[PDB]
Image (cartoon, rainbow, N blue to C red):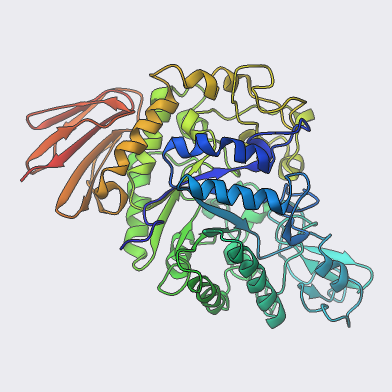
Length: 536
């Protein structure tokens, strides 16, 4: 039969900001354990927990100092084991982040490597002599600001960091690094985890020749996790990441995962051509799925969504797609796509729109509540990315403010002072509030997900788009003789178009505004959805 992850809805938890269970203002693993009943009650198929491993928190967990340990800020390894058991009991699968491409500077491996050029781990990180004039070896810049090379006086060499100075890149050309990486993944597989979200998976290998990246003209610059005005955008990223040698390494990773039937891999993939790289990385015998930033950016239109999903479908044959519209790195889609005054109708519509595309789905904590982006004041800024680029890019704190459980000042998230302040917008839309109003976003999302559970064409079916003029996105999902037409109004204004050829019958789609089809014409209010079945 078809794997559990094919079409699954994955709930991304950002642990720092989900539920604080001991009053220090920072979410923790016992808070997740306490809300596993709520998450299961959403109707999602799995959770993905962002990093909770031992970390100085310079990149809030993505700088890992011990790959096999839980940071005391979040709890203990025993806490994680209990979380696994409880989630499996409710029928949830549990995926965790794996950050394979770089470590914290505080990692024992880097503390050893950096000491001299001769120690047993000297070649485990990406070390390079200065140029003859003392400067970094090439023109690579960090995504998070400044050059990608940091001086180490103990070696009279630079080390590479694509991300923060505190995140030195591992040298995957080294066989011992590849083996140690696989062994760490095996450790978590041996605790029973169901899979892994693979952070920055195309960054594992760099070009050993250290070739300069070519310049990219201003009219070609396109941001994916970075602004087109970030200096990083001024280069074609051909040599600092996405190297051919990563392909046999993925095949090693997959071989390991094959030894644990049911374990799944989901790569985070952002490259010069993210869709093409996703297709290559999910070819047979490599990663099971990948997601990219293509639906995580400003572009929002029927033309854009149709063209993006169509190009991936044409490019990716053997892989299974995975789509997301919000996560811990981007402005929440409700605000990013809906604007400053996005209505709850828009929130419910965009979640149904996401879950009606072909592929597995990542749902970020709070999308089920329809939450808006927070406004983080300068004095509250935590994310180094935002501190570096303030004020033209304000960083990622706006989507990392705490989950609103109740409408109290602390929103039930913490008994102390939260590490980031609650958006005021959020406590008016808290879980405890939406849990009562039967017209809330939360109840509509649960209804849509339970409705989707009974529609195999939405979960496994193929997809085919109609060439519609703006603002309607219309397509077919098809599985097992069943065919399902869906039409979404992406605008807040009413719209009308001719129903496509064939014999179609309207079925009600819970949770979203209902548009009407009469004879051969469809007319949808703002952010309305028509779902029909093909009777013929």
